[PDB]
Image (cartoon, rainbow, N blue to C red; front, side, top):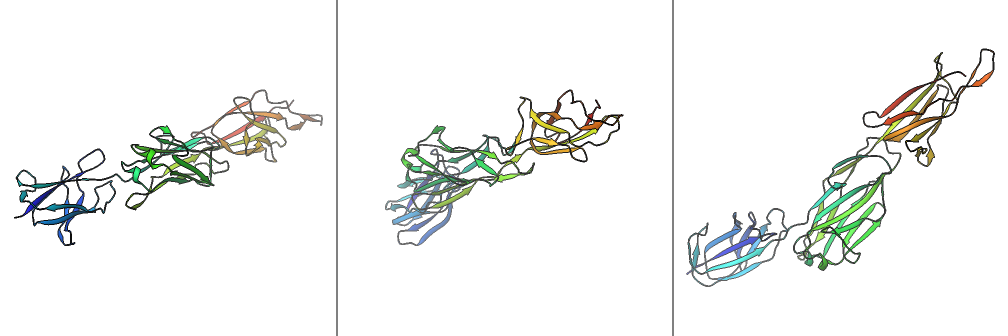
Length: 350
């Protein structure tokens, strides 16, 4: 006189769960079997069990799921058998369904789908942080998505939180900013019920002054605690943003004798005709004793260089005369292909 039991383990979409490991105990504690993995159909079939109360317990959660310690209790009081594959059944077989819940995940991308982004300073780009919302979110005690941005970055405005593409109120998820630290805490788990995706978007900018080609690595985190007080903490893969700036070096000479000239004044403008500003200061230069003007931290782009004041020379009769001002702006393009632009500018006597 002995009985059997059939355990059916499911997952997210009622999906059959393979790999979930259980041990079988009697009510009093004695272990009957250990290391019982659910097969390709989520089944664990056990037979030859004596009459009395039992309970399955999970020792290893199926991949991607939260370990659940809950005791799955049942009784064996009627005769029955069932083989490993379950093709041979007899008498009464105890049916038992156990549902497992996904552990939240976290993904971090730049501007939607990027892991790397070369960008000019003071230019908006988005950190898109997306995390999985489990089926049993309604019963979660804690669900926090946070990211502490690198010091060389500036948080632009207020970060937005979308639940399944739908922006939610501060009553649903509370967004706090403490310095570089953005924190999105779920306040109403009931409005989370039935939802699939948590989307924290943080708009950012790289500060000026950071050396070109600096790889600003950054990652996000999610903290959670479910109904069974199971605490978790996951960290995304790193995304990298890279400041792009170049160098413009002018060397002012006389057209005929090729001598270096000081006192030549220039200004860097953009194609629009607006003077370029780097760190609050207009980009102007005065040729030095070696005729050099060196402008650094110039963002990628197209510019025009204008002469605002000619250098001075002397005529064959000994009289300080100003050169004629250059007749045309000098087109310059700073890019990945041309990170350092070195120009020799000839001045003609007049």
